Image 1 (cartoon, rainbow, N blue to C red):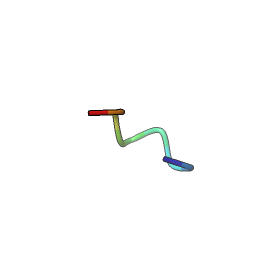
Image 2: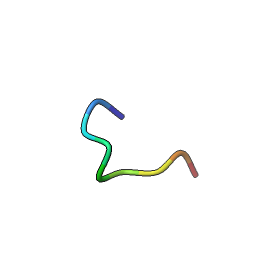
Image 3: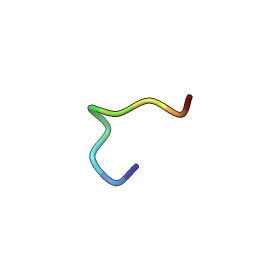
Image 4: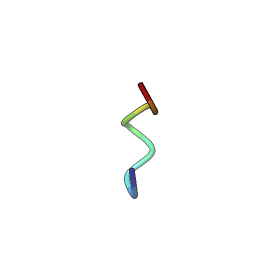
Length: 9
């Protein structure tokens, strides 16, 4: 994600 308030799931 570009926003890091998003984790690779």
